[PDB]
Image 1 (cartoon, rainbow, N blue to C red):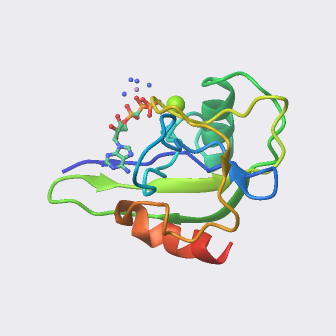
Image 2 (image 1 turned 30 degrees about the vertical axis):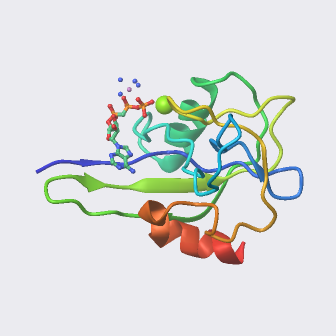
Length: 129
Ligand SMILES: Nc1ncnc2c1ncn2[C@@H]1O[C@H](COP(=O)(O)CP(=O)(O)OP(=O)(O)O)[C@@H](O)[C@H]1O
Ligand code: CON
Ligand SMILES: [Mg+2]
């Protein structure tokens, strides 16, 4: 009976290096690629919302955010959303990981093979990148 959106917007920028939570510790698996949440709500548009949710987390400036696409996972009583504002040129350090680690990830044109099926609706598009 509620709804919420997430102004994450992965941030690939070395070639396709996103600041995604990439198993900081050496993991035996490789599907630990979630998405730097942030919760869009500030202002009243995915711009001031994600952009302001961008600085409020780390504290950089650039990043050249871009929509690219977004999903909407529906739950029994949880209407969630997840704006994927993909950026590609942050200053020195990135900025987006919510309560997650968020770390540069040398993936290479995402494939969804390293990302969990949970965010299937958007990971399907990264696959194309
Ligand atoms: N993909 C997802 N699946 C399920 N729940 C999600 C989700 N993305 C976000 N949520 C949940 O929905 C809540 C959104 O409410 P908000 O309080 O507006 C977030 P927030 O506290 O403003 O931002 P924050 O993400 O920086 O903590 C989050 O606390 C999160 O737990
Ligand atoms: N910005 Co929050 N209140 N679920 N940590
Ligand atoms: Mg936030």
